Image (cartoon, coloured by chain):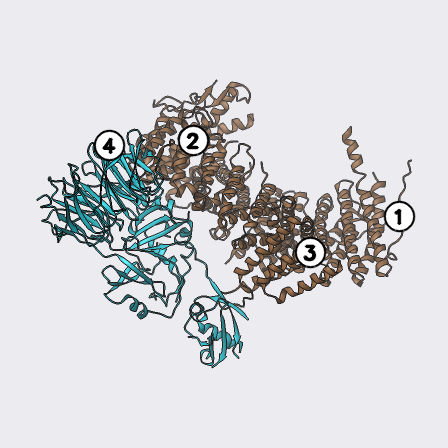
Amino acid sequence: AEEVEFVVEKALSMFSKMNLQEIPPLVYQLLVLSSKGSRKSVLEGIIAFFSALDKQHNEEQSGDELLDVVTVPSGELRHVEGTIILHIVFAIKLDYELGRELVKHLKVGDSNNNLSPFSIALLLSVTRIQRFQDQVLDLLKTSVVKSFKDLQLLQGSKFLQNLVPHRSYVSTMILEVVKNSVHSWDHVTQGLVELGFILMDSYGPKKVSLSRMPNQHACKLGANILLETFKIHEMIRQEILEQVLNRVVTRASSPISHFLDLLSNIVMYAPLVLQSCSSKVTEAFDYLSFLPLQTVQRLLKAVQPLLKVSMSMRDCLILVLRKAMFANQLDARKSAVAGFLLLLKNFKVLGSLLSVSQVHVDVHSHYNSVANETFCLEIMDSLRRCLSQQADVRLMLYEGFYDVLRRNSQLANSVMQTLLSQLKQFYEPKPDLLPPLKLEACILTQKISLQEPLDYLLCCIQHCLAWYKNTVIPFYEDLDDILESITNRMIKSELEDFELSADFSQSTSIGIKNNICAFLVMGVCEVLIEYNFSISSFSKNRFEDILSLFMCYKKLSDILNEKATSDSLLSMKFVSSLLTALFRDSIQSHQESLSVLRSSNEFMRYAVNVALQKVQQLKETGHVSGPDGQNPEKIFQNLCDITRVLLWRYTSIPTGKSISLLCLEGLQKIFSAVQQFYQPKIQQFLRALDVSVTQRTAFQIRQFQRSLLNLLSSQEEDFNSKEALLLVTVLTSLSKLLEPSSPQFVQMLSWTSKICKENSREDALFCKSLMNLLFSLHVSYKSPVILLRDLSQDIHGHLGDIDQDVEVEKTNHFAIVNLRTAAPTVCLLVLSQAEKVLEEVDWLITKLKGQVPNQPVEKAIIMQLGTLLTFFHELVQTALPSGSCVDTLLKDLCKMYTTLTALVRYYLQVCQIPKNMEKLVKLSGSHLTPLCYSFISYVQNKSVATAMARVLRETKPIPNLIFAIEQYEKFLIHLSKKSKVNLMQHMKLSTSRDFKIK
Amino acid sequence: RKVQVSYVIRDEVEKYNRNGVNALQLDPALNRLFTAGRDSIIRIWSVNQHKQDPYIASMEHHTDWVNDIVLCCNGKTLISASSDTTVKVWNAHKGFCMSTLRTHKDYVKALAYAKDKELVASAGLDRQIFLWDVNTLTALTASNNTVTTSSLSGNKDSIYSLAMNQLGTIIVSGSTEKVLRVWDPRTCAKLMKLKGHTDNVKALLLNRDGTQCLSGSSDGTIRLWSLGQQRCIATYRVHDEGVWALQVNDAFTHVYSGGRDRKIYCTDLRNPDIRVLICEEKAPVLKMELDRSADPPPAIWVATTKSTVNKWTLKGIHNITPLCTQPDQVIKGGASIIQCHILNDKRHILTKDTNNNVAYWDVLKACKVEDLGKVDFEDEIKKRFKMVYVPNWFSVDLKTGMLTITLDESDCFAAWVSAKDAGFSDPKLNLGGLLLQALLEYWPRTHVVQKGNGYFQVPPHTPVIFGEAGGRTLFRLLCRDSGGETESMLLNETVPQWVIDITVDKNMPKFNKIPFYLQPHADRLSASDMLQVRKVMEHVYEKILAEEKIELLCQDQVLDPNMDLRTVKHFIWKSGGDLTLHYRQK
């Protein structure tokens, strides 16, 4: 036994000296020798040796393509590592115990420095043995998730960054395992694909914060693994697409947004898709009729890059869509309309260029534009036949006709005539009959439901007509005259002509009909407001028509609101254009006409509120409802234009809610929305407001800093709490852009610290937000343990002492901490921050414990725990309220003593005791442990099945702390025995309590 | 399969055949002759003696040997068979391909025609015989492009000849089975199996009523068959070598035959004693076409393995010394490139043609550099020898008598060459990437606007061909036609990913490296293949002006400092191990 170990160790040393091409023969023989003897030693030596080769090769490869010192070429290194892996996997097949040692040796929570590109690639091919498939893939899944938690924890804390040197992460290792797999690593691909889908299946979004980011990173890694494996390996790309389409083509309505993005990325390599995995796309097309409308629209958009270059896929889709439309079954014609819309919204050229014994013939006929027009008109005529269907189909067509008419300018006449014919069914041509719209024909009675979205029909007509007059000009006059007639008769209507307050009930039939008719009138008024703004340019007469239309819109809105919603029909481009003229227009001619609109404060509120809706839709859904609402470049341009107006109005003139306050709300929403979606365009976003990102952000930050000072300079009763809360939220979001290693960040932290130290507000919510901003800035700068200690003293001074015979001196470090906010606002906030400090220290101790730089880390750990001891020392003798403050402090003391136990257990492994560790032990025994017993006594002495659960739940915390202290003292006895220094001389005898009933 | 990109280095107009002629068709209405050439081009000629230039048009859509052509529908439609495994329908009046039939799986060698029923059959090396109706094929459109296929079956070997009678009720097949199989095209049913030939059959004939059959085989014998009696009623041993072409008159009493022996005979069927030697050609006879304007036929057109097509008068056959000595009418032919040599730079090729002329070609620019005349080809190879090594990045095939250059994914980008070494004025260049961008220059998908690679342009008329390795032709077009609407959609379907990466995505191919370890003359290093020796000289200089004090040697031979390691490894190293260079002080 020992002889086998000795000879194996000798051969391990010979690895370095001998040639690499002789390694695979040696490993195969060494694995056979391993069977009758040591198994872990052989595997450890091979893995460690090849990991060093990988690391050395990576360093020498990184650099210019000039003369490099290349000890091993990349081509032969991957070939050698590949055949070593196959030998190990084949050995595991005939030796089950060899496989168990490999999993045990590479078992992960710790970083597991043993993991490497070679060891990860070894595990992926081991999955070809079904006996090890699940546990190996589970080992890899836990490794990447834990690795991302390490990355998240390091990024958020400056204290860890100064201590922990950067180490490679499992996510990076696996990505280059895929990259290295191009050297004929076909045995790794099978387990590579399964690992990618496990990451996506287990950590995909479940929309149906601490863990969401590592889950999102883990899910994104699976998409990267699958996408890169698709490009490189041809024998596996067919399986990848089939599994992706399986997850996407379903009626389950599960969140599949991440799978749809992977499908879109895969189909960007259309020749790769068409070559091998071509039938799967067509089979998914066959199931489009059975799928729901929302799935069809998202699936067809995902495979749009494939249909853009390929005619066969486009031709097959047209055949499926034509068959689905002719099908008598419903919910399939809706998908056919959606499919035909998407094809006609995106492609100007539609069309092409069997039985057992029937074959296709390659006819060499030149492309015919005239035949293409008839092909498009045939689909356009079919879509016109779908305008008499349910209101769901009508809504889709009205949204699609604008993009269809912009794409195919040759379909403009067909679309416009179709829109005109539909409008004639609901328009009264009589010059004096009121109302001009038949709102009773839009209602289908069989239960009352909406049949025709008349408001959406005019929105499509107005936008299509607007495109017509500025794209093809350089029936249209008939449409221009109808809209003017509609506008005049809607204004002169007295709201009684629409049969509208009569019932407005949410249950009765007449109330449902009245409620729907109320929405249509408001929707029509919005569209006519948009129409009259553009037509006749800036004329006073037309703007008076807009104001008259708005009053009709607002009066009906007030009636529905008080007796009690829907999206606005204004395009985001118009809202941006309306706001700019309504607030930032100084042209002499326009001022006369704009004074009509500006005089109505309710109109001012309406214009800003609709802009807030557009931003809110972007945050919720990722796109805006109106025209061009799914174009990221045009949404961003409107975001910049709206932001400029909102910035100007708020700052130039200070202060339902006021207009300036509403602009502040829109600014906060935009800043959050821009960072969430247009992350790479932040420099362009900040540029368009009127140096680098940090310099421009600091200019805006200082601009909002002055605003907050003005409210704080006001009186306590006059304090505008709503505005101050918004300013801190804006400052918090903007401060995410500053670089922490910059003077601009230091100024932001210094300003926040000064505001907290000097301003005393009675608003608990304002204090909580301000402290959260201060702690967010501070943690990325340095350890907040000194900040935490000073805040605990303020809570002690304001709330007094539990002794009731001593007087605690009021430090007054921070004025924001007053008698009202000291608890439960500040106390709960500082306890949550000390929790994060302990999690950081617990992470360090775990790394050191598995590691065996130690002396610098050990001193910093003791320094953190030493300062955090004084923070807890102040809180354990404070007369906290009996609510969640006591519950959280008791739970946090248990975490403090658990962390102390982990530090002591670390020295048990290392000390075969330094002064700093001894002084920490002495401090814990003189300033925390005796006072913990006093606090426990203080808490207990002073004072259906739901109550039964509550009383039994309250019996948990105090015994949990008692176990934590006794567990801590148990291991200090072990350390004193092992290190021969008595650490229990600093600890007094434990104090026990007994119950006695009066 | 893997898609290959190939192109032909040729002129815009190739008036004359650049290879042999496989088939002939004569149009009596317009006095037009059709030649199916081995250069993959069908040409139309005027048989009028007044015209000093008989050339009319070239019908260029095939990519390999055109084996058979039949003129149908009163000379309005031409059906062609080719070695590219396709059957194609043409407009014989205009000269453009209308449709392509891809039902065959091997070379298509024979075409049968029934004038009365307008029925055409195509047979080939895949042992399949397919029946087609010309009117159905001619009425095909882009929308209506489906055809029901009726195929004969029962042939256990590759068909080399096919025949139909005028009425379209009998079809005979000749193959390497050494037997003749007869079917009924109407019912697609077998009738009989004629036996007696001892070799492959390449010529078949039938009379108007379809009861007598004439066959010629490689054994050198002509056999007259009776379909009523299912037996060979006469055997004629006229030629010394195999018989490859047969022609008969309307009375079906005189047979005109020719083959490998280059001699053409007119044999009387009712008695073989009357045998007239019409002529003796300069090449083996591949096909013959009779002039049926008058009885007896005044002349016969002969196609051989040479590029020249000759007409021989038949004045006096019925009225050994050959009857004719010089052909009455001659259609000129070009020269076929028979030998090819790629120079050491992997950019220029020296070719020798059938006239012994030597020419200098530029693959990169897809053009001829200069003609050298009847210069010794082997001496010219040594005269243009250069001390440089470039990896192979293209392949050359001369099956059509023209320079066709093939680019495959495996080695298309294997040749990296510095611009200074080439004629372009040094940025580092990939020859395969530059050529692909020049071939797809007119493709709008490659425009991001600048056109092409910015260094050279292939001629706009260069035929660019996309096809599967050892398979079918996916798409064929000219270089200047990529910007068209119909071509762009076809290009999106057919261009493979490995060409998209370089021409559309504008990615750069890999940079190959050679690992070499320096050893002092009495430390492994990897570098670019085009790295010069001077760079290795200066690396040692810093380890221990650089050119003057340090000299490098390999295999006990001094190394040119301006020379690169790619050339060093290929020429001087002469070993299977990693390159070793020795540094010694000057």
Q: Are marks 3 and 1 in contact (CB under 8 Å)?
A: no
Q: Are marks 3 and 4 in contact (CB under 8 Å)?
A: no
* Helix, strand or loop for disc 4: loop
Q: Is residue B266 left or right of residue A937?
A: left
How far apart are the two marked residues, 2 and 3, measured between alpha carbons?
64 Å
Question: x, y percentage for residue A381?
Answer: 35, 29
How far apart are the two marked residues, 3 and 4, measured between alpha carbons?
80 Å
Question: Chain A takes which shade in the image?
Answer: brown
Identify the disc placed on residue B436: none
Q: Can you tell which quarter of the image residue B121 is in?
A: top left
Reading the image, the residue beneath label 3 is A34
Reading the image, the residue beneath label 1 is A991
Residue at mark 3: chain: A
Reading the image, the residue beneath label 2 is A336
Residue type of the residue flagged with mark 2:
Ala
Residue at mark 4: chain: B
Please report whichever mark, 3 or 1, sits nearer to the chain's N-terminal start: 3
Q: How many marks?
A: 4
User: Looking at this view, is A859 or A979 the one in front?
Assistant: A979
> Do badges 3 and 4 share one subunit?
no
Residue density around tag 2, few if under 14, some if 14–19, many if 20 or more, within 10 Å: many
Q: Is residue A72 left or right of residue B556?
A: right
Query: Residue at 52% of width from left, 78% of height from top?
Result: B521
Residue type of the residue flagged with mark 4:
Gly
Reading the image, the residue beneath label 4 is B168
Above or below — where is A717 with respect to B368? above
Residue at mark 2: chain: A
* Helix, strand or loop for disc 1: loop
